[PDB]
Amino acid sequence: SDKIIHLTDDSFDTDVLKADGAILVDFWAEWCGPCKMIAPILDEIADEYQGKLTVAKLNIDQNPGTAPKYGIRGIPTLLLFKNGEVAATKVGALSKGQLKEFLDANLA
């Protein structure tokens, strides 16, 4: 999480819903192995897209309410919030290339 924003339900309002720019919100949980697998990828992405994409992580174990709120199907769940509006989303993990493509395609 070297360059990742750890969100909470409480902070979600101001940090995501009242955001400006592109925020990639990765919903995760300690037990959800693949979240840990993508974590370094998300950090690399965060570094690569510094100032272009705000990479964020949201711990659902601590913040369950977010899952129902965003009809989360299963974690890891990446929600790409442009100014509080979900521009795109991804259920499950991604490879670095595909993730870069996905993000780039949204950022445009």
Image (cartoon, rainbow, N blue to C red):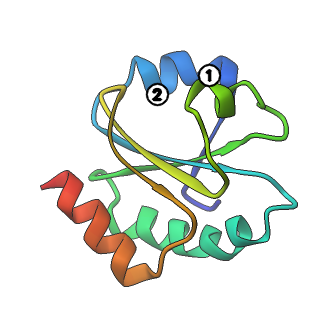
Residue at 37 percent across and 25 percent down: it is 19
Residue at 30 percent across and 61 percent down: it is 103
Residue 12: % across, % down: 57, 24
From the image, which quarter does the N terminus lie in?
Answer: bottom right
The image quadrant that residue 105 belongs to is bottom left
Q: In this view, does 93 lie to the left or right of 23?
A: right
37 shown above or below 79: below
Residue 39: % across, % down: 63, 68
Residue occupying the far left of the picture? 108
Contact between marks 1 and 2 (CB within 8 A): the answer is yes
Is disc 1 placed on a helix, strand or loop? helix
Q: Say what amino acid the circle numbered 2 marks.
A: Val
Q: Is residue 24 left or right of residue 83?
A: right
Q: Is residue 63 left or right of residue 5?
A: right
Mark carried by residue 16: 2
Residue 49: % across, % down: 32, 62
The tag earlier along the polypeptide, 1 or 2, is 1
Residue occupying the far right of the picture? 31
Q: Is residue 54 left or right of residue 2?
A: left
Disc 1 to disc 2, C-alpha distance: 8 Å
* Front in this rendered view, residue 52 or 80: 80
Residue at 55 percent across and 31 percent down: it is 70
Mark carried by residue 1: none
Q: Say what amino acid the circle numbered 1 marks.
A: Ser
22 shown above or below 95: above
Residue at 53 percent across and 16 percent down: it is 13
Mark carried by residue 11: 1
